[PDB]
Image 1 (cartoon, each protein chain N blue to C red):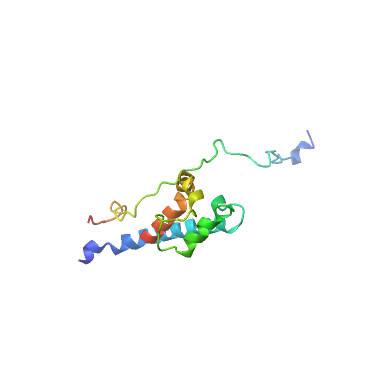
Image 2: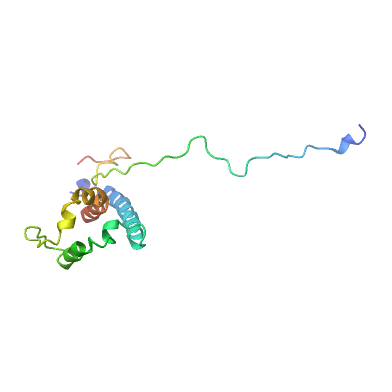
Length: 97
Length: 49
């Protein structure tokens, strides 16, 4: 039913949403590019092993048998979930768009 | 009196180089919202659902 499609509204809203997503991703990239504004967790030394291991196998998550490799991350998860929420939520919004 | 016949007021005023606004624009918190497709229903001859 062409009347119920509302293609005009869909297009005019998705264009603005895409512009906003582009702006947000550009800001995130600029923040994470220079080695001064990116989160300290990505430059911190003792936390380097955890990030490297996670990057080694990104699609799969295995926290059950970590072999004392994510111990450092296990005592600061509250800060990770308080500092990195914005970027993950932006990625989720991009996926929804 | 006889020389004042050829005189007009120069327009001269002094301001402050940069003038700030009465109230400064404040930051606005970002609130995540879902993609809503029913926001233009009140613009023109809109359709509902």
